[PDB]
Image (tube, coloured by chain):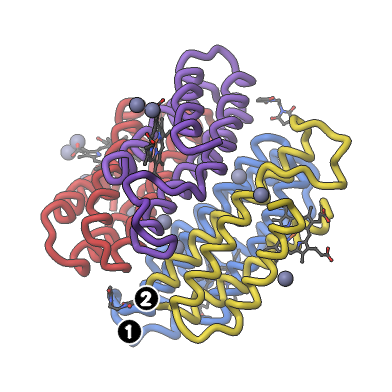
Chain colours: A blue, B yellow, C purple, D red
């Protein structure tokens, strides 16, 4: 999958999580988010097509994904404990990371 | 320090960070934040005086601090990297965590 | 709690985990480790009594605790997920963090 | 890149790091390590071709990558901070993660 396309998988699963009823559903939604993040990992964003893979601005772009993945990692443990509402809140809270990268590189 | 006291330290240093000029100032403010968070970890909040240290709400209260500390850890690396504005935004973004716990347990 | 003493709580519970039988035992051992680390957080080590709270060396000493706490945080989730052996391995593996700090500052 | 291929990228850059002189070299090697880890994340290992992507076994295989990635993230901060030797030692210490997974699923 491509960048914008991974981003839509991130967006749709966030919606899936918000609305879910049970631990297995968030389980699965977060799992798909993790894969999408992992895929996005090496992608070059339109805004930075000029920059090299070594620039400060590529390094900082990627860093945003480390944060996201670490946060999906944690939400997933909460899910795996059947702290369903707790996992939804963590899912909701990670929008701060989405936003922080969008405001810089999108 | 007690829990309200640690919270003030957190709120104050956030202000310090927002307004700061150089890396050393942010470094220092985050460092104090990290100590306050570390101290607050063991505390019992008024709202849960009547629950047990082993409660769901106690295990979830504590968890918020691990999030915050992890996020202060990261912002500090940015500061140490002279990515000052980057560190200020990370500082800014962890109000998400502050708020999430306040809504629940304040 | 004073530093060496927190360290002994860290060492004793590591033994406890290594030998445990059930999830609840490891839960409790890791919980106590977490509190010990959180207390140790701000302590000044003998080797650095002449250094300032702001020095590079104090910052780097503190950093080691960030790592330990984040690793205890993770191991705890594994315990809470009834993945007992997985949690014992994670407990076993964070000896690397113990060691890395001892070799520098002990 | 395939699983075995990502593993060699991991092993090679570890060497590169061991032997390095300056921080850009470590920076660059860790960066490549993170991409390899990110790519590997989705892989199915030969030992579990017969289990399902939903298994206890697959969930636990994947978890090891999150650990490794989290550890590469941290070591990279150290590199970015010109704490070269510190970054080398962190690189070295994450062999504990490499080994833990190999003992289990290689
Ligand atoms: C976090 C969970 C997250 C979500 C959700 C998300 C979604 C998303 C949308 C909905 C878009 C709009 C693109 C469009 O054309 O409609 C979008 C675009 C970009 N994002 Fe994103 N995205 C999330 C996270 C992140 C993170 C963590 C980063 C940076 C590390 C990031 C970056 C970007 C970039 C760049 C784009 C634009 C890409 C382009 O080709 O125009 N996003 N994402
Ligand atoms: C995050 C950086 C954070 C900030 C900032 C913050 C601020 C803050 C203030 C200013 C108050 C008190 C206002 C008054 O007039 O008394 C306050 C109080 C509480 N907080 Fe807080 N706080 C932050 C973080 C967190 C986190 C992460 C938690 C839980 C995980 C948490 C909890 C609480 C609680 C409980 C109180 C009030 C308890 C009391 O004895 O009054 N805070 N915070
Ligand atoms: C990690 C899990 C960990 C263990 C285990 C550990 C053990 C330990 C002991 C048992 C002592 C004192 C022996 C006694 O009973 O008298 C001790 C002392 C020190 N440590 Fe340690 N320690 C662990 C973790 C860490 C970490 C993460 C750091 C660095 C940030 C660190 C450092 C030190 C230092 C310095 C001492 C000297 C204390 C003293 O003897 O006065 N340790 N440790
Ligand atoms: C950590 C940085 C790490 C290193 C280093 C590493 C090395 C490594 C080598 C050298 C091989 C040999 C491959 C070959 O046949 O040519 C290898 C293979 C496997 N590894 Fe690995 N590996 C590191 C990390 C990890 C982690 C985190 C896991 C699990 C989460 C893991 C597992 C495996 C598996 C499985 C193989 C075998 C693949 C195959 O032979 O088809 N490794 N690794
Ligand atoms: C979340 C709700 C629930 O019932 N379970 C099962 C209980 N459980 C443990 O206590 C440890 C593993 C486990 O399944 C949940 O995880
Ligand atoms: C803070 C970040 C920074 O880079 N510097 C000065 C020189 N320096 C680097 O540029 C990279 C490591 C290093 O010491 C700061 O003072
Ligand atoms: Zn689009
Ligand atoms: Zn957690
Ligand atoms: Zn106190
Ligand atoms: Zn004040
Ligand atoms: Zn970071
Ligand atoms: Zn002693
Ligand atoms: Zn002794
Ligand atoms: Zn984990
Ligand atoms: Zn590949
Ligand atoms: Zn092979
Ligand atoms: Zn081969
Ligand atoms: Zn191949
Ligand atoms: Zn760090």
Residue C5 in sight from this viewpoint = yes
Ligand 1 within 8 angstroms of badge 1 C-beta: no
Both labels 1 and 2 in a single chain: yes
Circle 1 residues within 10 Å: few <14, some 14–19, many ≥20: few
Eyeballing the image, is A64 above or below C23? below
Horizontal and vertical percent for residue B50?
A: 88, 35
Does the residue tagged 2 have its C-beta within 8 Å of any atom of ligand 1? no
Is D3 on the left-hand or right-hand side of B3? Answer: left
Q: Residue at x 27, y 41 (%)?
A: C103
Between A7 and C51, the one nearer to me in the picture: C51
Q: Find residue D36 and report its image quarter.
A: bottom left
Circle 2 — which element? helix
Q: Would you name the residue on which mark 1 appears? A: A51
Point out which mark residue A58 bears.
Answer: 2
- Residue at x 57%, y 25% (from the top left corner): C29
User: Do the residues bearing badges 1 and 2 touch, measured as CB atoms within 8 Å?
Assistant: yes
- Chain letter of the residue carrying label 2: A
Q: How far apart are marks 1 and 2 (CA)?
A: 7 Å
| Disc with the residue nearer the chain's start (1 vs 2) | 1
Q: In which quarter of the image is residue C32?
A: top right
Left or right, A69 with respect to D48, comes to right
Where residue B46 is drawn, which disc sits there? none
Residue at 73%, 58% in the rendered image: B5
What residue lies at 77% left-to-right and 57% top-to-bottom?
B4
Asked whether, in this view, residue B23 is left or right of residue C24, the answer is left
- The relative height of residue A4 versus residue B46 in the rendered view (above or below) is below
Q: Residue A59 placed where, x, y %? A: 36, 72
Neighbourhood count class around disc 2 (C-alpha, 10 Å): few under 14, some 14–19, many 20 upward: some
Kindly state the secondary structure of the residue where label 1 is placed: loop
Q: Which of D43 and D64 is in front in this view?
A: D64
Residue D92 lies, in percent from the top left, at 24, 45
Percent of width and height locating residue C75: 52, 34
């Amino acid at each position: 999958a491509d960048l914008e396309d991974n981003m839509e998988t991130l967006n749709d699963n966030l919606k899936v999580i918000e609305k879910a009823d049970n631990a297995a559903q968030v389980k699965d939604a977060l799992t798909k988010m993790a894969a999408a993040a992992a895929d996005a990992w090496s992608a070059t964003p339109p805004k930075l097509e000029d920059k090299s893979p070594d620039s400060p601005e590529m390094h900082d772009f990627r860093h945003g994904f480390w944060i996201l993945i670490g946060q999906i990692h944690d939400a997933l443990h909460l899910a795996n404990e059947c702290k369903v509402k707790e996992a939804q809140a963590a899912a909701e809270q990670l929008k701060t990371t989405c936003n922080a990268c969008h405001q810089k590189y999108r």
